[PDB]
Amino acid sequence: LLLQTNLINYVTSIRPNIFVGRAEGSTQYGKWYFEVMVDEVVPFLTAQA
Amino acid sequence: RPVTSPGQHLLAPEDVVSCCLDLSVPSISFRINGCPVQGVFEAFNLDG
Amino acid sequence: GVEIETISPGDGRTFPKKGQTCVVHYTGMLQNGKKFDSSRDRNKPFKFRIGKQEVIKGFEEGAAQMSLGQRAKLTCTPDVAYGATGHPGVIPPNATLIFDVELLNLE
Image (cartoon, rainbow over all chains, first blue to last red; front, top):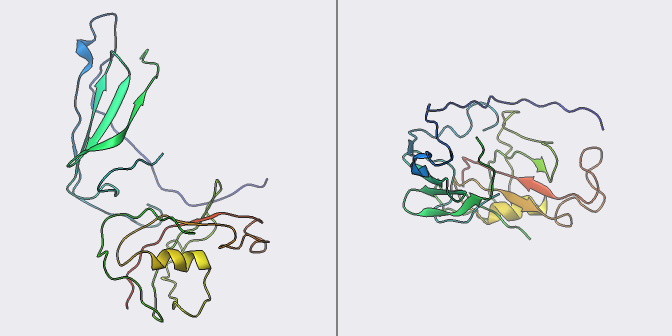
């Protein structure tokens, strides 16, 4: 019923400029693969996650 | 929506994660270090 | 009673033993609700000794089923938790409680 308050951290994101899509035949056969690496933990920086 | 898999944890340091997509049939499947995860997505619009 | 979903890193062998202190960094969460209590924002470890029967049954039960270093997603039922009338003024009646704990406890 009443309003609530809480601290909250940022959530932000970035993209490669890698565009694809199912066209009417020139879809470039719809097949790409991801890969990521992380070299950190930092489970609790200040407060939340 | 948790998924059962071996080696369950958050994104630990020194790990590999990836994915694969098919535009023919909507099928988004993921995988991690060692083995793939037991969960995919399907049946979504792809008009963009 | 308790159905944890642990997380890998940590020792994973040194279980708690009776009559000893257990540091935590619990952050409460209501079922389909909001945060109501936490110690990370308060910056205090919240030491407590198992065996004296002062903390809630579900929290100590979940702490019993784990060991040093490993994070977890504790779940508690209303009967195990406050859910007969509820903790007054904060928890409603017939609640179902969630917790997640990290620690650097001595033994």
